[PDB]
Image (cartoon, helix red, strand yellow):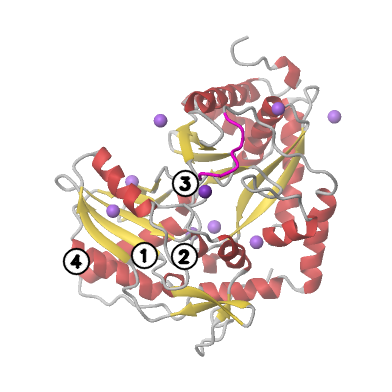
Amino acid sequence: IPELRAGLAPRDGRAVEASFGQSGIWLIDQYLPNPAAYNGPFFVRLPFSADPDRLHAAVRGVLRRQEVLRTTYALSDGTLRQNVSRDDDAVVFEVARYGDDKELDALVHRVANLRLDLARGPVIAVTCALGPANRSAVICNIHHIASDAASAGVFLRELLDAYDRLGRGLPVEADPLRPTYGDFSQWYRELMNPEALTRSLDHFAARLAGELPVLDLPTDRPRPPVKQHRGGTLPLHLPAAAADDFEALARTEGVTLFMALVAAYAVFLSRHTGQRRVLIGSPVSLRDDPATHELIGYFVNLVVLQQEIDDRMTVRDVLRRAREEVSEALRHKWAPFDKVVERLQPPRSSGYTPLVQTMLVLTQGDAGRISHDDTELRIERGAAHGAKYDLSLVFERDSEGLHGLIEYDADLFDEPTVRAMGDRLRHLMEQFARRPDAPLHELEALGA
Ligand SMILES: [K+]
Ligand SMILES: [K+]
Ligand code: NA
Ligand code: NA
Ligand code: NA
Ligand code: NA
Ligand code: NA
Ligand code: NA
Ligand code: NA
């Protein structure tokens, strides 16, 4: 994997082709809601009362430092291009007030429900929310084509740095030595040369050959002819003790926390659906190179994980099988998801996604929190989304430990059905940590 370098893309004004990820997203763009919440609009509670004029000036400084925020998109001769403008004020901005969490969440909903224009911009919105004494919040929506979950922490770190510099009368300008998203886009095209691309597409095409299962969860409603894009969320409420034993389980069995979550979720899906084979999508970060860690952009590729489950496997068996599947997938993680779909030529339907109908995410680092000025600031996500998937399981591990959230499609589910699912999943995860040797058929269902 070659290092990413600044200037790989022409610095002479010519528009770089959109990245593989961006191309996939632009082709989907209707005026639909954000497809998921975990990578969508976000806010941060600040322990001071931000000055609005200086905060707006700080935002302009972030636009100057983050070229993807100044990028719009257009087809030119059959190629989707990244057109970069010099307008550092291309942001949907407002100053508003809140006196309690309800009023703050109302401001969050207004930002979160914006439908930003990829051809004309802006591709970012920021609200400076002024709260009760010494409290304020920054609310932000960066279009999916221009961001990923980690971009939220990158944005806030850059914003707060700029706010502080401006306060001190210091300049806030682009770092010419940092690579751009345009540089990354060209680097990725060079990495996916014809041989390398064919090799990774060949891998998934073999792994995922034949008649793939379509997730068959019990639902409260049949899938409707007209999808309404109405996403819900519900906390998993995984006890802190079990969450800690689950992390210990992963460590002692020699798998990553993500591998163990994949395994537990696959057993949950297999039980609920009745299906032996289950497919789980996961958005894998492409920020391997430290040169990408301070950039806003779409540095993710969706991979498909296939698991087979039966009730004579042990907890340990399914952890080890998750380890093998995840290990092999991550080796081939640069093969763009939409090209995998194209190779597999799935039978696609309106409403249900290609290849995968559910996802599992583990939120880490800049997607969940930052430190600024020796203060830990949590990145909080809005709850509105378009329910691209039937269900998404979004996990995060903080100091109190690991916690989870279920993003779900309200076209299919009433909330008490999702609460029941979440109860069964957390129960399974607690059993995993207690009985790693047990055959799955000995892990009794909740309420037996
Ligand atoms: K519709
Ligand atoms: K980062
Ligand atoms: Na916060
Ligand atoms: Na707002
Ligand atoms: Na609720
Ligand atoms: Na079923
Ligand atoms: Na990322
Ligand atoms: Na078997
Ligand atoms: Na893609």
Residue type (three-letter) at the residue carrying disc 4:
Asp
N-terminal label among 1 and 3: 1
Q: Nearer the viewer, residue 194 or 434?
A: 194
Tell me the quadrant of ligand 5.
top left
Q: Residue placed at 48% from the left, 75% from the top?
A: 178
Please report whichever mark, 3 or 4, sits nearer to the chain's N-terminal start. Answer: 4
Vertical placement of residue 237 versus 333, above or below: above
- On residue 385, the disc is 3
Q: For the residue carrying disc 2, how many other residues have a C-alpha within 10 Å: few (<14), some (14-19), or many (20+)? A: many
135 sits to left or right of 329: left
Q: Residue 106 sits in which quadrant? A: top left
Query: Cβ–Cβ below 8 Å for labels 3 and 4?
Result: no
Mark 2 and mark 3 residues within 8 Å of each other at the beta carbon: no
Q: Secondary structure at mark 3?
A: loop
The three-letter amino acid code for the residue at tag 3 is His
Q: Which mark is residue 331?
A: none
| Residue identifier under label 1 | 158
Tell me if label 4 and label 2 are in contact, CB under 8 Å: no
Quadrant that contains the N terminus: bottom right
**Residue labelled with disc 2:** 296
Residue at figure coordinates x 41%, y 52% from the top left: 41
Q: Is 332 located above or below residue 228 in the figure?
A: below
**Magenta: main secondary structure:** loop
Q: Is residue 307 left or right of residue 259?
A: right
Q: Nearer the viewer, mark 1 or mark 4?
A: 4
| CA gap, disc 1 and disc 4 | 17 Å
* Residue found at x 52% / y 59%: 30
